[PDB]
Amino acid sequence: DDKMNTAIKVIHTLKAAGFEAYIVGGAVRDLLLGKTPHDVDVASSALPQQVKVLFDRTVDTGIDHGTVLVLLDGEGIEVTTFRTESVEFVLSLEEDLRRRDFTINAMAMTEDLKIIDPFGGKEDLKNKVIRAVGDPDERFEEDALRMLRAIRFSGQLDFIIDMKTLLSIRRHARLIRFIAVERLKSEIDKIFVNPSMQKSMAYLKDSVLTRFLPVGGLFEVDWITYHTDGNPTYGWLYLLHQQKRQFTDIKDYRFSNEEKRLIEKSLELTALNTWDQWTFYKYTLKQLEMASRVTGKKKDLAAIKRQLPIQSRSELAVDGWDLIEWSGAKSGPWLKVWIEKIERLIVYGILKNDKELIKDWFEDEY
Image (tube, rainbow, N blue to C red; front, side, top):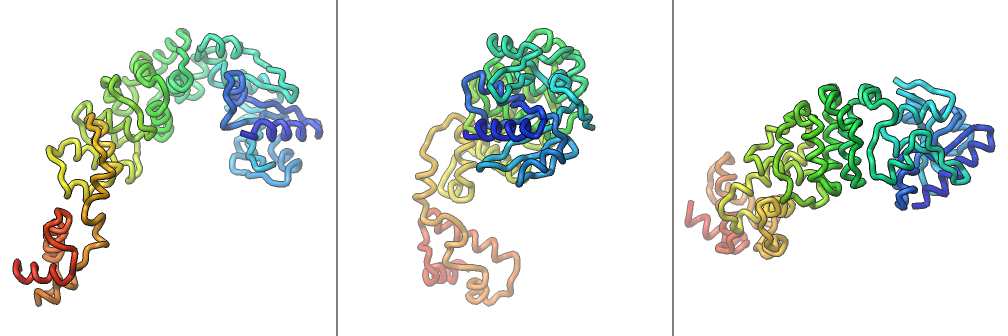
C-alpha cells in the first residue's frame, strides 16, 4: 500500500546524502501495469553500511548480498547496492539492470517518477511479452531457475514468452537439474495458484522443462478441469489423482509433513468408496474438502462434520484407565482396540457418550 511513498522517502534520504537511488524491478513493473506493488525494492550507489548510517532501524540479514531492509513509517523497504551475481558490487545502475532476468523487471524509476528503461521493458510490458534481458543464453546460464520463473510470470501476468527467450529455455532446460528443489517447488506453487495456469503448464512442457525437472513428466496431465482453491497443495493432489499415483512419486520436492499429510489423506479419501460418519469424524475438513474437490463432488462437508455426535477423541467420556478398572486386566495395547470400539458406537450415535452407560455396554461386551 503505503510502500511507494516510503520508498520515495528512502530514496530522498539516500540522495540527500549524495547517493543515487531508484525504485527498481517489480515495483516499476507493477506500477506501469496499474497495480499497487506488494514489494518495493530500491537500488542505490550506497554500500550497505552507508545505508545503515542513514536510517535508525535496519535489518541486516541480506548484507552480504548488498541488501539492507529499511524500517520506516510502518513499512519495510529493501535497499540494495548496485550488484550482479556470489555477489559483486557494481558502480552504475545499468550494470545492475543489464543482468536481471526479464525486461519488464529491468526498469528503474527516479524520485520524480521518470522511468529508466534501457532494455525496452516499457514496450515488452505493453505487448505482454516476457523476454530475457540481453542474451537469454547468458541470463539462464547465470541462474537456471529463471527458465522456470519465465513460465511463472507468463501465468501471473497473462503474458506470452518471447520466442527467442523460449527457444533459449529449450536449449538450456537441462541446467534446471542444478537448482535446489526448494526454489523449483516455490515457483511451481506460485504457478499452481496463479491465473491461466493451463498455459503455464503448456509452457512447462513446450520449454522441455518437464523433461529435466524432478519427476517432471508427472506435470504433463490434463489441467483443464483443474481450478485452484488458492492452496498450491491442491495442484500437487490434482496432479497425483489424475495419474492415479501416490505421494511417494513427488517426494523429491521436499514437502512439509503437514502438506504430505493433507495430500496423502486426501488421496485415501478419493479411493474410499463410501464415506460415513466415521469418515467425517477421523478426517479433517480440509482433507474431506480437498478430496471431494478433486473428485468433483460438491456436498456441504462442514455441516456433516458439525452434525456428528462428537468432534474428536478428547470429548469421549471414557479412557483406557476406565477400562482397566472395569476389566480388571492390566494396561496393554488392547485398550486402544476397545476405546475405538466404543468411539465408533458413539460417533455413529448408537452408544451415548456417557461414562455410566459405556460401562454398562463394556461390562456386557467384555
